[PDB]
Structure formats: structure tokens, C-alpha cells
Length: 143
Length: 143
Image 1 (cartoon, chains in turn brown, green):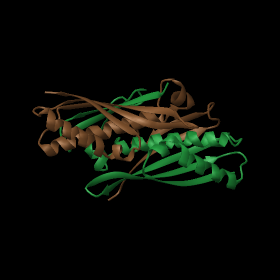
Image 2: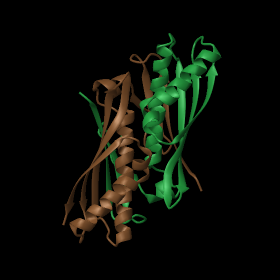
Image 3: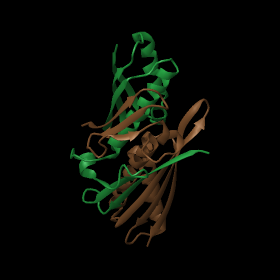
Image 4: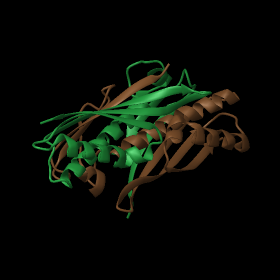
């Protein structure tokens, strides 16, 4: 039972002069513009880094819920940010690190066991596993 | 310095019962909903896989434009899709594969040299380099 999900993108002409769009099969991203400027300069807009980050935060959050559930707890709220770094490395760029920042609220859990759980979610979630980048974890745990 | 791009997500409640939302720092994704139903139960909507697929397709298309540039060419059109495999492996799932498909239109390049170029981009773009999954290439080159 292999699951398939698709993303798409379009591009025209030159590297820095060119225009591009990214799409998602669910429609969430119809044909959002993106180009060399939103990736390497600073102009606000999508780029691969940001989508990957969204993907990471999304997968990790689901996973945290999952691991907690197996422990008999139910997150009331889970809020996480995934900051993706695109560093100049050698003759080019590489996505070297992804900083996971998460604020989680869960009824009754002792720090010790919760810490164990988030580590589990952090290292085992599908997206963490497929990424060869350096992944760190920062989190505040309410009550 | 180093380029930083963020992605965000929110999760409330149970794994199977809970709801999630995914965001982007650019805005392109505000608080699109996702869940164990659109991730694992074929229902239409976002999921981590599709976002990774979008990012990869986008990064690779840009890379291809770049390598065509270093060769003295300018793609008039690049249409790529990234099919992401989320496979049930062992005691869970893992993004094991990404099938890249691209329809490219470039003025006057011999099929040989161009072949050497898409291959270059396929393996060299940052996103391909960060992903530890198997990555295949399928393409059609017009003229």
C-alpha cells in the first residue's frame, strides 16, 4: 500500500530573469509565483526552503500527537515553526539545517516523559527521516 | 549571511480525530487544513508529501534553467511533476521515493548534451541533495 502525493512547478527562460510557478495536487497551491529573487535575494514569496519547512513542521506536529496518544495523552494544542537554512557551501548552496521550534500544551505530563516523547517524534517522523540536514529542537511545554 | 525561510503548523487533539493547519512565512499558505485523513486516507487536501513534492519540483526546475544557462541555452518552457512515495516500511511509513517527470522545451540543443544537463540538475539541485530518498528522472525534450 504505497501512497502517492504530487507537487508541480513551471519555469520559463533565464535563471535570474526567469519566472516560475509552483502547484500542489490538492490545489492548496494553484500556481503561486516564485523565482530566483524569492529564493536567493530576499523578496517575500515562496521558495523550496519554505515549502520544505512547512512540510517538516506539519509532519512533526502530527507525529508528536501520535507519540503522545500512544502514551495516553492528547495534545490540546501543538504549535511549531520550521526554520530552513540555505547556506553557501562549496561551489553552491545546500539546505544544511532545519530548526524546529514548538510550543506544546498537554494536560498532565511530567517534563521527563514528555521530553522523551518529543525526541521520539523529532527523530522518527517521516519528514525528519528523509532529510539529511541537521535538525534541532526547541520547545516550551505548558503544564 | 545564511538564508532562512520558515514554515509553520498547528495541531489540536487526537491523531485520527485531531485537526491540523499548515502555514508559510510568505503567506502563500495561510492556514490550510490537513490531517491523518488527507495524509493517510486519500482525502483531498494538503499533506507533508505534496509540499515536499512542490518544493522539489520547483528547485529542480530552477536548477535545470541554471544548467541550461551555463551551457548557453534558455528553456522556453519547463513543466515538472514530483510524485512522492510514502511507503509503509517496517513499523511505519517513510518517504522512500520521488519520481521526477518533466516536459522541457529548449530552442536548439542536441538530445545528447541536453540529456547530460537535466541529469546534472536532477542530482545537483539542493532539494535533491537534501533528500535521502530514491530519485528517478523521466523527461520529454521538444526540439
